[PDB]
Length: 425
Image (cartoon, rainbow, N blue to C red; front, side, top):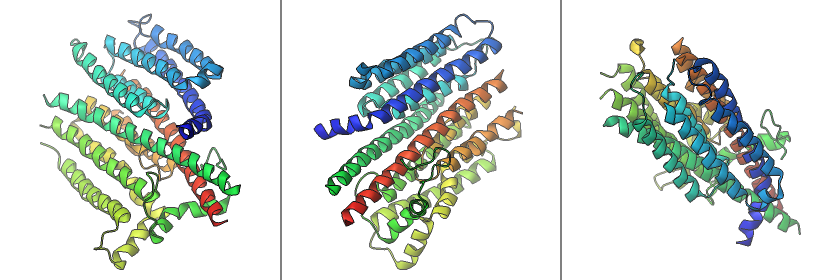
């Protein structure tokens, strides 16, 4: 229990910076929504922008708490106080709904707040999972009960399938963040006992080029050396869960889209069938690079490490991480003018790019902007202005989280190589 305390007080500055950035983002979402609310929803202003701006000063106060020595003692409590406040504001914003707001706007709030609770607030797993699901079940319950009929069975299943996707991504994001945080602390701990961040903010590469080059092939040489899967952060085993997560996210997100139709276009069946065929093959390789059954030969191994290379993995991982995105857009046709479902579903397709932490964050985040958010944006070409603000906020969260988890998995590898280096000495 003392080593977990020691881990906490060493990792606490990361939790400080993480939580502080969430306050800046939550206020930015509140500020941006206020400006949009003040122009396209002038019918009810003092009730729709006042809670949004009142939360702005709350974030400043929560920012003020951060420098206080009392926050250093109970930072878990401080994050809990914000989480309920952000929960209450978002359900309140969903309580009310020219005088109407699209559902995708509310769904972005539900998704964005959930990702904050799971990834940036450092609450316990049981608290984050139960509080998140309780918020998700209350978000859906309030919407179905407090909906407006003036403007707007299997539908209920679609909500759980969609909300199941984010919780799966959120818990995977939180678990991966925890195991890398715990592993990095131990390995620098072993490094300091053996003796007795070199990452540029922009490009996210090790400042030492030799370390950068060995980083790229590290997963490749992991397969060639056939390193046994030791912990949850092993590069080969880490790949298995993200490939697994891409399977579940794509399966359910495709299940919802097929639920709306229950004739699907031949483009819908073709992309899903290829996606399932690629997913089962990609999933099979992930379990085969980890478990290495007795049926293995050298011929199949040679292509196994070949895939593990830096470039080809980004070639296949880009398709894999985007496969939920192409699943949604295979269900669109010329009869688009239907739009609420794809917008809500594409909200999770762009969310899914937070997966595959091994891949470069810049590739995944840009793919989300270009292939997971872009096709819906120019398809529309105020609902149009809303989805622009909706996807900008979610992408901004996706872009930032990919930045934070990449440097986490980068610094985890830095701790391993130094710990491995000190073991050879």
